[PDB]
Image: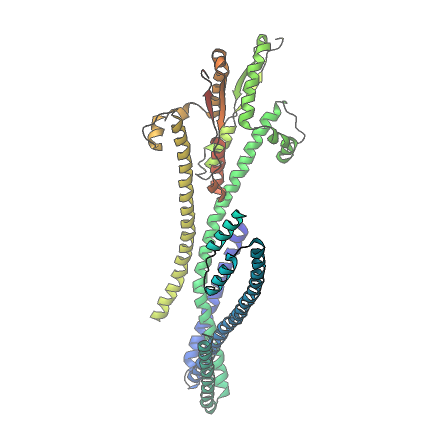
Length: 147
Length: 196
Length: 147
C-alpha cells in the first residue's frame, strides 16, 4: 500500500503536469487560432473534419449492425440445425417405438394380453398429444397380477 | 429480424457513401483558396487545439479521480499500518508469554522460534483440547490428594501482568485479539512440599 | 467561456462525487453485510439463550438481552468460565460422596455450527466466529434419581 501510495503520488502529480502542458498547448493554440482565422481556410478545414468524423461514425454504426447481424445469423443457422436434430430424434425414436410395438405385441401374444392391440390402436388414434398411458399401465399391471 | 437489420445496415452503408462524396466538395473550395503555407499552419494549430482540449478535459476528470484514489490509498495504508503495528506488538506479547513458561524449565525448548516451538509440540493439538485438559488436570489434582496429603500439594492460578499498551484503544476491530490473549493469559501452576 | 467553465467545474466535481459514491456504495454493501452478520450473531445468541431457558435452569423477565444483562449484570464481573466450570466439576466429585447411589452424570452441550457461518466474512468477523465457537459449549447435568 506504501508502494501504491508512492505510485499514486507520482501519478497524480504527473497527470497535473500533463494538465499544465495541455493548458499551455491549448492557450497557444487558441491565441494562434485568433490570428489564423483571418482567411476562409480554417472554417473549410473544420467542416471537412466534421464530414470525415460523420463518415467515421457511419462506418462504426455499419460495423455495429454487421456484428449484431452476424451474431443473429450464426444463431439462426444453429437453430436450423437444432430443428433438424430434433427431427432426427423424432425419426430415431419413432422407428424404435415401431419396433417396440412389434415387441410389445409379441409379449402380449405370449402372455395373451388382448388389450395390447386395442390400446395400441387407441394410441394411434390419439398420438397427436400427451397420450395418457396410466390406464395402459394399470391394465398390464392387473394382467401381470393375474399371471 | 435478420432482413430488417440487414436493410438498416444497407441504408447506413448508402449514407456512408453519400457523406464521403460531400467531403470532396469542401476540398474543391479549399483548393481554390489553395494557400498551402496558410493551410499547413492552420492544420497544425487545429490539431494542437484539439489535442490540448482533449487532454485538459480528460485530465480534469481523471486528476480528481486519482486524488480520491490517493485518499483511499492513504486511508487503507493507515489501517494497514495500524494492523502491522498491532500485530508486531501482539507477536512480541505472545513472545513474552511463551518466554515466561519456558523459563520454568518444566518444558524444554529446542529453539526459541515460535514456528520451531510449534513444530516441536504440534502433536498435542491432536491429543487434547483446552476444556478437556483443564478438566483432567482438576481430576488429577483431586485424585492425587489421596496419597500425598502429607506433602500438602497445592495449585494456584498463575497469571501474567497485562502489558500496558493493551490499554490503548486500538478500536473495535482489535478488541477481539486483546480479549483472546487476556482470556488465555491465565494458567495454572502446582507446587508440592517434599522433605522441607 | 461560461459553458466551458461550467463543464470544467462539473468535470472536476463529478469524478470526486462519483468516487465518493463508489466508496459509499462499497461501505454500504459492507454495512449491510455487517448488519446481516450481526443479526445472525444476535440470533445465534438468541437460540443459545432460548435453549438455556427451555431447560428452565434460569428464570428471566422476558426473552430480551437488555433486561437479562441488567438482572445478571454483576456475575460476569465476578467469575470467569474456566473457574466456574472447574469448581462445578469439583462440586460434582465431592457431592458424589453423598449422592453416589444416584449415579450422577454430566454431558456437554454443543451447537451444530450453523451453516450461515460458511459465507466467509474474514478479517473483521473472523475473531467473533472463533470466539463464539469456543464459548458456545456449555456443560449439562442429568441425574439418575430413583431410576
